[PDB]
Amino acid sequence: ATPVRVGIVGTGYAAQRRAEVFRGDRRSQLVSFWGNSEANTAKFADTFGVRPQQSWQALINDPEIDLVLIATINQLHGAIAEAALQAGKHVVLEYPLALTYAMGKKLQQLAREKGKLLHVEHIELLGGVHQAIRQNLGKIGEVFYARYSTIMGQNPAPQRWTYHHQQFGFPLVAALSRISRFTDLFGTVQQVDAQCRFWDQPNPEYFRACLATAYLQFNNGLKAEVIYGKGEVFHQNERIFTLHGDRGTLIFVGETGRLIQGQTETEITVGSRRGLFRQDTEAVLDYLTTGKPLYVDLEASLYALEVADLCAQACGYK
């Protein structure tokens, strides 16, 4: 039903990219938003000339909203999605979908029972690099060894939700989502070993550093290392995504990529996350206005959630 009236829960990168396209597209209208922190809420309201709702609960219950975009504090995503679906809203999330596989399945069933969209993508984190990997995996043959490491030194560690044990949640959730979206080629994860180490702040509800490591064995033979570290103890940053195959190696350093085959080295064109967010937003608008089905289905985010549960279980986490 046009225009699609949108409320945005969140003010970060994913929320801003969605807001830009919702505004620009004539099939949609940005009505309200909610932010968790005072300064970023003010900036978002100014950029997009939309007034903020004081609570996200009020936003999702607004009768002048058709669609809720969720891209906020990690812990909140499942609860906000369930509340929005119960209020008869369509829901689009930036991954995570929920805290547990069971909640993700409960959300999937609820959206079906209400006949509402439940759509999840994972674009903000290395979305362009992921498509570049997809476009070039066919070139390197059987992938047997991959390493995805994100190390971000930060001193002092802030007292915000990203360093808060409960709000941030299991630290490997986002990284494991990235490594799990090649099931089409790697098969499913068959074995997991994972460790998680924290450096607590004086207030033990916050950590000042974390190092989480997951070592995965896939069914088609791939051994993958997935590393997530941030905080006060890290003196060298690292943003590496390397995949070794018997016909070549793909190396991504940040958003920079290079194909290596024999003695040749080729630059890899990495597209913008802005373009990927726009195509996804326009596909969502297509579905809501003409019923044309989305190419993405919830199964990819559900499996990433399963992998996260499995690695947390291997960690003794929660």
Image (spheres, rainbow, N blue to C red):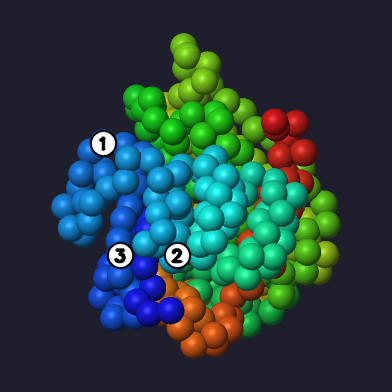
Identify residue type, mark 1: Glu
**Horizontally, is 233 left or right of 47 in the view?**
right
As helix, strand or loop, the secondary structure at mark 1 comes to: helix
Q: Residue at x 45, y 60 (%)?
A: 68
Residue 106 in percent (x, y) is at: 71, 54
Identify residue type, mark 3: Leu
**Horizontally, is 241 left or right of 61 in the view?**
right
Q: Residue at x 36, y 68 (%)?
A: 5
How crowded is the residue under tag 3: few (<14 C-alpha within 10 Å), some, or many (20+)?
Answer: many
**Horizontally, is 50 left or right of 242 in the view?**
left
Q: CA distance from mark 1 to mark 3?
A: 20 Å
First of labels 3, 2 by sequence position: 3
Residue 275 or residue 208, whichever sits in front: 275
Q: Are marks 2 and 1 in contact (CB under 8 Å)?
A: no
Residue 287 or residue 96, whichever sits in front: 287
For the C terminus, the quadrant is: top right
